[PDB]
Length: 306
Length: 306
Ligand SMILES: *[C@](O)(C(=O)NC1CC1)[C@H](C[C@@H]1CC=NC1=O)NC(=O)[C@H](CC1CCCCC1)n1cccc(NC(=O)OC(C)(C)C)c1=O
Ligand SMILES: *[C@](O)(C(=O)NC1CC1)[C@H](C[C@@H]1CC=NC1=O)NC(=O)[C@H](CC1CCCCC1)n1cccc(NC(=O)OC(C)(C)C)c1=O
Image 1 (cartoon, chains in turn green, orange):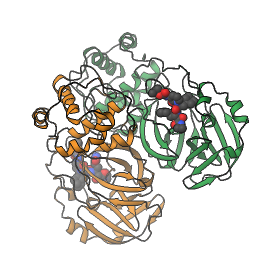
Image 2 (cartoon, chains in turn orange, red):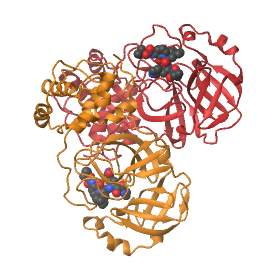
Image 3 (spheres, protein in one colour):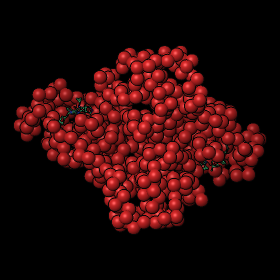
Image 4 (spheres, chains in turn brown, green):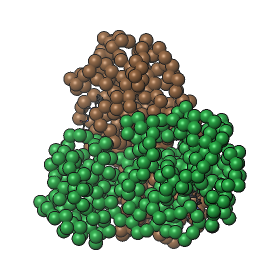
């Protein structure tokens, strides 16, 4: 038992991290097969960043304007292309530590592991969620650009995030591994801000199931609710509306615990209306929304503490 | 910016994890050079566990009563010895992925990364603290025995924890890599329980410094306090007494933020007496005690958001 924000083991990803330099700018890139991926703003200086024209900044570079380092070893770049907001650098060596991998675009509310890196050197790993407002509440300092987010399924690494920038509120924005931003953000220094966020309702419910699997039932009640009565309360508390799809996703957990989804919703509505009264759930005094239903089944016992 | 419970990248440790079987019991072990370390209770069956005599249970095993698997590859055991609550299995192959490493016994209040493993396969990584009561609030299911805790300094892995058991409250107990238990616990099924825990005062203070480095000052005040006046309040709130040594450790953070330690103590005393009033610090509504002063300097900017 116990319940912790757990990250995926980071080994398969550590073996892919490199340093990419272009003039004065050093950041991290990702080395799979004979390609190195990195944020395209590695070609920018400070002043370039107010209003960069990337096509224009890139045409005046060569293969040799990019220095790639895997630990000690310099890698020779022999090709370059822009893909959306990344650069693809073709390199003379295939990464021998290339894991089985895929590139996925994760959906808001989904979770992944971030390997925070500086100068191609991994410094730390943590789990976080794609917020409904398409940001992440990361921990990132200068030099962290190029750090990746990923999930692991069996032996297959699903890369889903590359870090690009911090927004004014201190939250983080970036791209999938095709270089498309998550959210409405662009890779220029402008007046852009995180949209208003909302609580991930499906995750809070998954975590209440986690708390019951772990043998805690204090916050349950004898009431039920309609979806629509739940959603009127959800809106007032800045929670995402629950849908039948989200009710269907909570099925397995519902069955494992024998608590119907709409009963757990009655419990949540009561938790939202009456607070927790200095009480805790799985050690927390707030309602946690950065665990998916999949994260709960992954980490929890397949047999309830009844 | 941002602040997250960050773990060390787990790669160096993943490459050391193996499966150890003895009759019916399978758990994890750690393969450095030509030794495999694992909990000694791997030689026990269910009934053995009420009152095992390990010396007696071990003398009736041979080298070949132990099956060691590194992925596919079976390793041949050619030696065995008990060291306190571990077994050392000498093995015919030196682990080629052996990192530079050390074995340390960490002190209560210190933090480390756990690589949760099942059947020698790493499943997840998370950060936690050695509690003053010598337990950890881990996340561990059946099969997790042998999972290790570690810190990384440059390229050197400091192993400090091996998992052995869950106590009645759902918290976890285990040994250093010499097989000495942390706390008063023994590797038998008896009526043993976690002692009463206390909040790690030094860590809470380090985390308030983190919140100020990150540009939040709301909870500060114009008061100061004596150590002794602080400690009278600490005792009533089940916080550890603060000492001059702990004041000295907070020096660097004190200087980086220009807030004197006893002023931050006045802030904490006020936070303890008056609660937070639905306010947050680095996103939390409770006072966090699982970051050391070292963890804060590691993760935070070396320049304050003034
Ligand atoms: C990234 O480029 C990087 O690390 N590059 C290596 C040379 C160092 C950084 C990483 C940021 C910085 C702090 N945490 C991070 O996440 N990215 C940037 O600095 C941003 C550069 C981008 C260039 C093109 C895309 C848009 C910007 N960048 C630039 C300017 C301002 C911010 N954020 C910011 O001003 O900080 C706070 C919220 C306002 C105080 C930014 O990320
Ligand atoms: C460990 O031996 C293991 O995983 N072995 C592989 C064959 C599976 C487990 C891991 C525990 C179980 C659940 N989470 C974990 O941390 N360790 C044990 O099961 C304990 C065996 C020890 C044998 C010698 C040392 C003392 C016990 N063990 C045995 C009995 C009871 C508990 N805990 C317990 O009863 O659970 C809760 C708190 C009471 C509900 C225990 O860990």
